Every structure is written in structure tokens, then in C-alpha cells.
Length: 258
Ligand SMILES: N[C@@H](CCC(=O)O)C(=O)O
Ligand SMILES: [Zn+2]
Image (tube, rainbow, N blue to C red):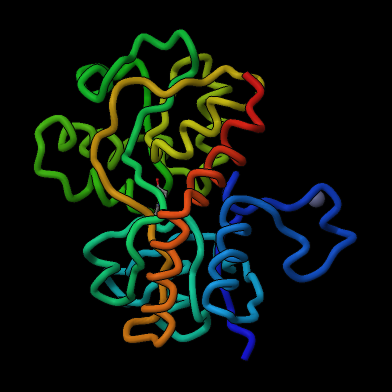
């Protein structure tokens, strides 16, 4: 009866509450997706348990083993019933799991340490003094790997062979690297994460230029799952009732600091 909700520790979607070590189950976490899961469960009328994905990855298929990892994998192999996280709706994922309509709209963006002489993707691509990377094994890395647009093809060419590696295991590592590189490192991440970090102390980063693409995050369920329909309708109702807007403001700006 209790459905398993796989998710990921990514701020401000899912974070450990101040005194998580003193708590258990769902009470250990807080964040946009923790609230979203609560609201969805309320409309779908289900009991659930949040589960942080073991490998801490979003989801990608190994070209060799063909095995899916991350949250996508938890769904594909039946270990999770639903995924409530900033999981990007992509073609390859849509082929193996189901997605609700978007609960958040975003695009790939550029994060720089304030003062960095960069204003666009073209600016990064035409130079090598400033290094740049992305989260490893996510939709952003795939974007550059698959792009047929000149400027992005140039960027992938650089990152693909960059040494040391410019692909971080977590968004947090990417941000830390930007903050510690004195402006010699820029990070490619989704606007949502970018906008959030920009509102947090030391307030030393900022999003520059427009987004590289336009897409969205969706709540995922195993392909053909009976929860897909109810979850989709729940997402649309939350959207139309302004709750998604309320949650975004709550976790991004109301708790602003810059
Ligand atoms: N939202 C992305 C992860 C973040 C990123 O790749 O920038 C995904 O679902 O893979
Ligand atoms: Zn702790």
C-alpha cells in the first residue's frame, strides 16, 4: 500500500532538515519536492515513503550494459513507484518511463563567479582561459553530447577531453568549484538551480545570458503505471491552483539572502 517515492538530495528540492539525525522517515527531509510529494499524495490519496536514490544520480543508460542508473533506473527496475524530483523530461527517458506534464519550466544556463568576463555560451566556446563543465550523467551533459549546433559542438569538444575532468558528481561540487576558482571556472546547470544558488550567501555567483533551451521537470512513474494518470491530473491541478508558484517562491525567494 505504501508507495516508494525515489528522489535526490539536491537543494532546494530535497534537503536534510536541521535536526534530521534526530528524526526518521519522511520527517528527515524538507524542500520543494518534499512539499510537492506531500501535495500530490494528498490528491492521489496515497501513503508514501521518500527514498533518496542510492547512487545519487538522475538517470542515464550505460551504452555497454544498457542498464539504467539513478532514479530512472529505480523506476525501470521496479524498485520505486514514483519519482518526485527535478527530473528533466527527455526523449530517451520518455521511451522507458512515464512523465507528468511539467511542474516547473527551465533551461540550461551558465553560472559564473561574479566578475568573470563571460556573458554567453559563445564567450565560453571562443576561449580556453576559463574552464567550464556540467553535472555528470544528467540531461545537461547529454545536451552538449547530442547537440548539432556549432557553438555547443565546440563546447562538447572541449569538455569531453578536458583534463582534469570538468564533469562533477553533484551540482554542489560544481558550484563549489566555481566559487573556489577565482573566476577561472564556469558551470553549466539548469536555470532553476542557478537561480537558487544566486540567492544564497556568499552571494558570489550569478546567472549570465539567456537559457540554452526550453524544457521542464516531470513527476515520473514506471511505463504503464496506474499512478500516471492521477499524478498527471494532480500536477495540473496544483499548477492551476497556484501551488507550484507558491512553492517556488517559498524555497527560492522568500528565503532569499542576497
Ligand atoms: N535535471 C537533470 C539533472 C541536472 C543537470 O543535468 O543539469 C536531469 O534530470 O538529468
Ligand atoms: Zn546533518
